[PDB]
Image (cartoon, rainbow, N blue to C red; front, side, top):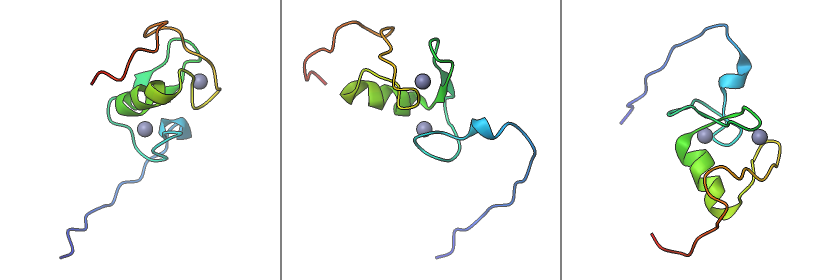
Length: 72
Ligand SMILES: [Zn+2]
Ligand SMILES: [Zn+2]
């Protein structure tokens, strides 16, 4: 199977890219601290293991000052 489709080129801020996904974004959740762009799942996932920013490495104490147990 091919299932191959693509062909899009534009000129805009190269920041759109994700420091994690290293590609396109989905939710486009911007931080209110360092003002960085990170996919909801990305920033949310990174906050699960590390309460810091995978960009500047800052302990963003916005979501919650508590780590919390392993309750799904
Ligand atoms: Zn991402
Ligand atoms: Zn940051």
